Length: 49
Length: 49
Image (cartoon, rainbow over all chains, first blue to last red; front, side, top):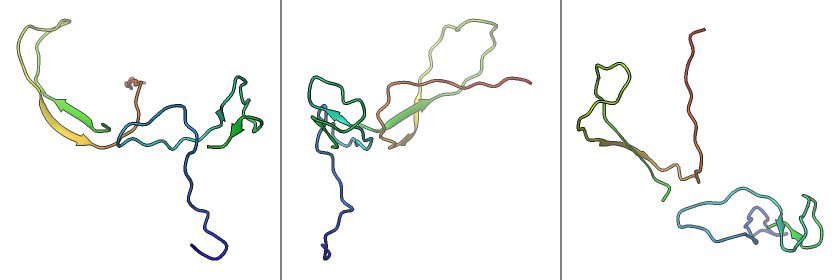
């Protein structure tokens, strides 16, 4: 916790399902929460996990 | 659970094109904790020029 803050720590917010014990998830992509495909560009209902 | 279990056994044969009738077991050899989700596989061969 340095002056100005430390930002080398990241975590996933949104997921399509639950995980299994002793299994990892490192691949990143875009997540769609509505009825319209995100088309790979950040927009409404399109947030980086 | 991530663990990759491998067994093996070695035995010669005198045949042309078949699977002979008989009994033989397998024994454990080596285990590595790769721990990657897996759903497919393939195989590689060799050719003589």
